[PDB]
Image (cartoon, coloured by chain):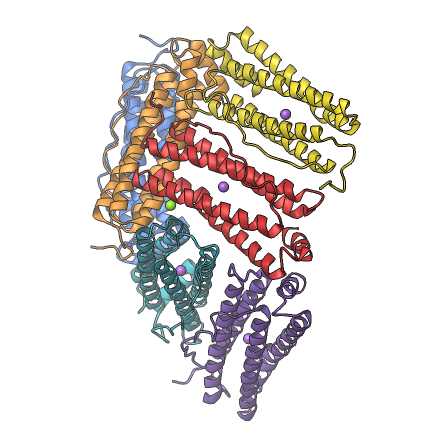
Chain colours: A cyan, B purple, C red, D orange, E blue, F yellow
């Protein structure tokens, strides 16, 4: 049953990796939903749409890298349902950015718990995988989203549709 | 409630489009599972893995095009859970190709039902959308997968691991 | 006696580095032996030979990087005899790949023990050195060798000399 | 009061980062002093001057990267006075190199203490930040300075003004 | 004690140059503080941050040129502590620009006093050094900052966060 | 048991080739030791280090060519332990060059004995192999090392650390 390549890879780490794969795919689905919300004719913020679509693809890449990790270590991928996002209607550019920030912080928390598990299981390869490919990415993404939220709020979003328009043009464009 | 752009777009067509979006995302997920099955150290068919990963990305593109359609017509996207694939272990290159063929034919059947609905609702734009972007793509994909299955079987798959190896090299490579 | 550059570098870490240097040089020697086994007129698998020669040179590079590390930290290199490999005759492409896999996993285990020692001695520089330059390299090498072994076995190695021939051509060539 | 981006960032880590920022700015100031010492007409070692000026700019870059880190994590930068260097007159190329070596080892010790704090606070992002951007840089800088000191001493510095002259030309030039 | 190069260089001029060096380094530190204030996630005005970082580096260059002057004339550099800036929190783009304007005018006043001292000591080289490299630079910087302050105020800064946003984009970007 | 390619290849020649392979690998190991001795922070002669590392790689190449010869003639490679070098600490650039000269002359003597054996066994292919690839290489290497030793001694090595420094720069650099 044991993979010929498997070495120093705890069952709990394998399971946590599978959970993280699902979470990354979920985040990719959330961002896809947000993108096409901004593609609606009654919202019509193309650069918001582009931004979130890019994020969706990035999240898919993160999931695929975790799957590659899983196979590299000799764990076995078990996929689960990708739950639909919490919203169909994301209400505003600002609200979407706030939800994205919340999502990214939740993903970061899951990564931190993964790192803690790796450390506890004395899995330095896994620890450094997480550190190299995920943790800084998360910190950067959270910082960027926080900057966006700050700018939108200062501009007067979401009540100032001019605010969101000009943010779409000048920041995301 | 009615979109300012909506014209000649029946509620039943909108719902069928949402169902098709989910089905395309499901197909993407299935192909992703198959790809990383072939990435396992105990399977190790890199070109199978690459082939199915490409298919996964293509299916995601198809889903995104349907979402774009939905917004273009003034329908509203409602996402649903993406169900996990039927298998974790796809057993062989031949079996994966057979399951892919079955999946593609099911997707094609759903597209044909969508076309029939469009026709019944006198939606020529939707009909020609399906015809232009989906139906021929499906016919081609089904033909390609059938060719692959035929070749693998004639080569002696899945019992001939040499068969699958050489197919991976010479057809998919 | 203490090096002017030495800081936070435990004697046990220095000794473990010297042991790792010897182990990497040993691995280089093993791969050299395997390469020239495949260069024999009665074996004559040129791409196996090339593959293992490349591995030999890579292992030498790993040893040299450890020696550089040793000097960077102000430890002192103490070389030991490089023991001859366990075999003169490696029997088959498959057997050589299996022995290489075993060797790489042993090297990985030694690296993991080195990391554990570094961590216990609160040597984050050493830990991150190992993580950055060695651990992922090992995981990748083990995964690659496992893939090779899997393919050879499925093809019918080592009894199918056609198997090894075609693997030599299509995978290693 | 809490930053919207802040996550898993302990107050003690934030304070230690502020201390490190000050220390890096101090090191920059020290190197600036040394550079312009070597620019004096009665010292006139242009390549020493260039070397230390480069080091000064590098140290400022390190400080700026720590400030960026601070903002990325949602900590708040609090700057302090940059103390003047211990010397106005650095006496000789050899003495300046010895003081630089001492400074770099002190900076390294502060970084190691920072890493220990990060580890104790279970801040893997901070740990890997320090490891990636600072610790190896320090090890390299210390090794280089030790090499310089060794060469100068063997050449006969600081009593051999010919020694320092030729070192300036051939090593630093 | 007297430098072999020293000629027509009064002790009072040497001391005033040392004071100016400290003042330029102080200005550099102030601009650095402002830059990283604008890099905060709750301020998030990247082009303000870039503008002030550029100013910081420019001020450092000015200090280094004064040190070079000091050595060229045969005076001796005596560095002092670089005091921390008056603020940690610069409140707004407009407020930062107003403080920068005040700082630049103070630096200009110090330069004018330096020029007056040079003139009184019949040091035409020093006078023309100040005139060529510093005075026009100051006049330009003050004019630019005044223009910025005027624009921000007319736009409605600092109460109009849209004002600061659009200024950041269109003037500083 | 006899190789299909073997012709006019005496068992004694095969054994002598195996001994020469071991000797070349030993020489490679010696040069590696010397290189990293010069990489020490308390020795710090980078061009000595580079010179000996190049020699190490060259010696490995010589060993690999002998192994290739062995297989070409249908002999069988039997590897032995590579003994550690006689020294951990090579004391000086001059001493390392003197030891290298001694090593190269010992290798040359072994090659001459190999040639004599080949001649006695009427193996003109082996004789011309040795002549073409090894003997002139040895003569050149010995001449070069003798030149180096002569220069170092005339310069005042090893007591003149300036001597070794300038030799490192101007001859080996
Ligand atoms: Mg790390
Ligand atoms: Mg003038
Ligand atoms: Mg505008
Ligand atoms: Na992600
Ligand atoms: Na599709
Ligand atoms: Na290795
Ligand atoms: Na630094
Ligand atoms: Na200035
Ligand atoms: Na040789």
Q: Is residue C39 left or right of residue D166?
A: right
Which residue occupies 31% across, 20% down?
E77
Q: Nearer the viewer, residue B4 or F35?
A: F35
Q: Nearer the viewer, residue C149 or E117?
A: C149
Which residue occupies 75% across, 32% down?
F9
Number of callouts: 0
Q: Quadrant of residue E24?
A: top left
Image location (x, y in percent) of residue E21: 31, 26
Direction front: furthest residue: F1
- Give the vertical position of E127 relative to A9 (above or below): above
Q: Is residue E39 visible?
A: no
Image location (x, y in percent) of residue C36: 64, 40
Image location (x, y in percent) of residue E90: 25, 46
Q: Nearer the viewer, residue A131 or B77?
A: A131
Q: Is the C terminus of chain A in the top left, top right, bottom left or bottom right quadrant?
A: bottom left
Q: Quadrant of residue D113?
A: top left
Image location (x, y in percent) of residue C149: 56, 55
Q: Is residue A166 left or right of residue E149?
A: right
- Give the vertical position of D41 relative to C24 (above or below): above
Q: Is the N terminus of chain A in the top left, top right, bottom left or bottom right quadrant?
A: bottom left
User: On the rendering, which quadrant does ligand 9 occupy?
Assistant: top right
């Amino acid at each position: 049953s044991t993979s010929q390549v498997r070495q120093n890879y705890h069952q709990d780490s394998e399971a946590a990796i599978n959970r993280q794969i699902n979470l990354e795919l979920y985040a990719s689905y959330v961002y896809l939903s947000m993108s096409y919300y901004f593609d609606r004719d009654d919202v019509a913020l193309k650069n918001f749409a582009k931004y979130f679509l890019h994020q969706s693809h990035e999240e898919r890449e993160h999931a695929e890298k975790l799957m590659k990790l899983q196979n590299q270590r000799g764990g076995r991928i078990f996929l689960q349902d990708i739950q639909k996002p919490d919203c169909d209607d994301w209400e505003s550019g600002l609200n979407a950015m706030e939800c994205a920030l919340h999502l990214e912080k939740n993903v970061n928390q899951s990564l931190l718990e993964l790192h803690k598990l790796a450390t506890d299981k004395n899995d330095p390869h896994l620890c450094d995988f997480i550190e190299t490919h995920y943790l800084n990415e998360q910190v950067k993404a959270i910082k960027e989203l926080g900057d966006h939220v700050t700018n939108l709020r200062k501009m007067g979003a979401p009540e100032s549709g001019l605010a969101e328009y000009l943010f779409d043009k000048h920041t995301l464009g």
